[PDB]
Amino acid sequence: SPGTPGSRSRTPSLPTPPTREPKKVAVVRTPPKSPSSAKSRLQTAPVPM
Amino acid sequence: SIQFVDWCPTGFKVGINYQPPTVVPGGDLAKVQRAVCMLSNTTAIAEAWARLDHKFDLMYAKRAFVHWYVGEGMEEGEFSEAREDMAALEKDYEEVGVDSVEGEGEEEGEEY
């Protein structure tokens, strides 16, 4: 007997489309900034002359 | 040179008692046959009242400690009412120092 039987899957292969890469790695842009504000402040005179 | 006001026509008052000063235990005076109390009314104290009125101003300009008083039910108008009264006084103590002058300008002689 043939030692690899017919009981076994013989599914024939297909036209699979071409392979895309795993990762894009497109270029980044820096995020924007404005400068930090002082939190403790200068104050005016509460009392006049 | 113990300067009285220039206007002064009279400016002394006398009073005389036979009892001397008395010694108290723990006391600091010597035992003496005679003594003098003196009360002087004078224009000079008025500058010491400008010291105190300047000591008022310098805090009031900062409303320093002011809140301790408003909450008692009197006003910041009630400081300035009493402050304006110190100014009427300062300005009248000046007036009773005046050498009976009630003039406006000054006048000069002939010099070389």
Image (cartoon, rainbow, N blue to C red):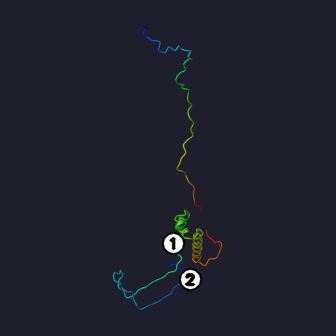
Q: Secondary structure at mark 2?
A: loop
Q: Are marks 2 and 1 on the same chain?
A: yes
- Residue B20 figure quarter: bottom left
Q: Is residue A2 above or below residue B62?
A: above
What type is the residue that disc 2 sits on?
Cys
Which mark identifies residue B48?
A: 1
Name of the residue lying farthest toward the top? A1
What type is the residue that disc 1 sits on?
Ala
Residue B49 in the image: x percent, y percent? Answer: 53, 72
- Residue B16 figure quarter: bottom left
Q: Residue at x 56, y 82 (%)?
A: B8
Q: Chain of mark 2?
A: B
Instruction: Work out how far the residue at label 2 is from the one at label 1, CA to CA, in angstroms.
Output: 23 Å
Residue A46 in the image: x percent, y percent? Answer: 57, 59
Residue B73 in the image: x percent, y percent? Answer: 56, 71
- Lower position in the chain sequence, tag 2 or tag 1: 2
